[PDB]
Amino acid sequence: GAPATVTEQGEDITSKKDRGVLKIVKRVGNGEETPMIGDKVYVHYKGKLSNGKKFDSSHDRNEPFVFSLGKGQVIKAWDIGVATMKKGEICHLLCKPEYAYGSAGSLPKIPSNATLFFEIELLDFKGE
């Protein structure tokens, strides 16, 4: 399924080249520009564990997830991954634990040492 495919066929987008964050572009976005550091980004997402269980989805809330890019407001894999996206893009992101919740996890749903799968849609980005 999709998690296996991004694991086996995804692009390493880390600057360290450690395969900690893998990406596949699923829907091509608009033009060329990607957000810049500090922009207010609006996304929809769904996340799953490696046991197949969905842990969260913004679609279920009828509102986007909003954060300031490149400021450590989200897990490392998201700062890295969302920075590569075009407006309107949908991607799949595989996040090894060192770029996610590490040994701590996120209690109760995300266990220790968890590799995470996300589908992410970049809705919009704005400077303030």
Image: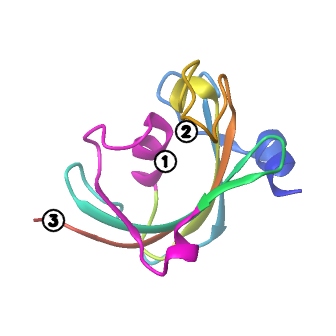
Q: In this view, does 113 lie above or below 116?
A: above
Residue 110: quadrant of the picture: top right
Query: Which residue position is annotated with label 1?
Result: 81
Q: Quadrant of the N terminus?
A: bottom right
112 on left or right of 83? right
Quadrant of the rendering where the C terminus is positioned: bottom left
Determine the image quadrant of residue 12.
top right
Q: Tell me whether circle 1 and circle 2 mark residues in contact (CB < 8 Å).
A: yes
In this figure, which residue is indicated by the disc labeled 2? 13
Give whichever of 114, 71 is nearer the camera.
114
Badge 1 amino acid: Gly
Answer whether residue 65 is magenta in the image: yes
Amino acid under label 2? Ile
Q: Name the residue under label 3.
A: 127
Numbered tag placed on residue 43 in the rendering: none
At x 86% / y 46%, what residue is drawn? Answer: 4
